[PDB]
Image (cartoon, rainbow, N blue to C red):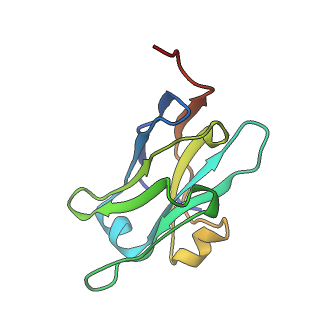
């Protein structure tokens, strides 16, 4: 593991069914030349893969998400901002965790739980039971 710039934000507290968008920004060469991914670690549980984007090809990338978040979370780059976003719609209580960004030389490594950089501080996501009815 090596210390690479990682800025992580977007966490917060929302009721089940709410949404948040996470942001991971890194330096430009790291952003372009590595696959980048989001992981999460819930209280009492092992850190696990959430979603990833591949190394940039000449004019594109590809994306994968964990089965448990399919249809709810969308991962994407904003190439202009060196940022990997995780749009989290329709959050569930079991999505509560600290979310962490990392990188690896290819997307299959991230999918297996592997990564290459020192971890940042992450961003805390708490999905509560619900909210008042009106």
The one of 112 and 5 positioned closer to us in this rendering: 112
Residue name at image x 63 percent, y 26 percent = 129
Give the farthest residue toward the right. Answer: 44
The one of 132 and 107 positioned closer to us in this rendering: 132
- Tally of marks: 0
Residue name at image x 42 percent, y 60 percent = 75
Is 89 displayed left or right of 1 in the figure? left
* Residue 15 visible in the shown view: yes
Q: Quadrant of residue 59?
A: bottom left
Give the farthest residue toward the front. Answer: 134
12 to 52, vertically: above or below: above
Is 45 displayed left or right of 131 in the figure? right
On the image, the x and y values in percent for residue 131 come to 53, 20
The one of 55 and 85 positioned closer to us in this rendering: 85
Which quadrant holds the C terminus?
top left
On the image, the x and y values in percent for residue 115 come to 59, 65
* Residue 6 visible in the shown view: no
7 to 39, vertically: above or below: above
On the image, the x and y values in percent for residue 71 come to 50, 59
Q: Quadrant of residue 57?
A: bottom left
Which quadrant holds the N terminus?
bottom right
Residue name at image x 73 percent, y 36 percent = 43
Residue name at image x 58 percent, y 77 percent = 108
Give the farthest residue toward the bottom. Answer: 58
70 to 109, vertically: above or below: above
Is 113 displayed left or right of 13 in the figure? right
Is 59 displayed left or right of 67 in the figure? left
């Amino acid at each position: 593991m090596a210390e690479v710039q990682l800025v992580e934000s977007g966490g917060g507290l929302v009721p089940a069914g709410g949404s948040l968008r996470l942001s991971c920004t890194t330096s430009e060469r790291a952003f372009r030349s590595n696959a980048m991914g989001w992981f999460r670690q819930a209280p009492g549980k092992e850190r696990e893969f959430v979603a990833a984007v591949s190394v940039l090809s000449w004019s594109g990338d590809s994306a994968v998400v964990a089965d448990s978040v399919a249809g709810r979370f969308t991962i994407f780059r904003d190439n202009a901002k060196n940022t990997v976003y995780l749009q989290m719609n329709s959050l569930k209580p079991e999505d509560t965790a600290v979310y962490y960004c990392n990188g690896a030389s290819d997307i299959g490594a991230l999918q297996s739980g592997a990564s290459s950089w020192s971890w940042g501080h992450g961003t805390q996501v708490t999905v509560s039971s619900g909210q008042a009815g009106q």
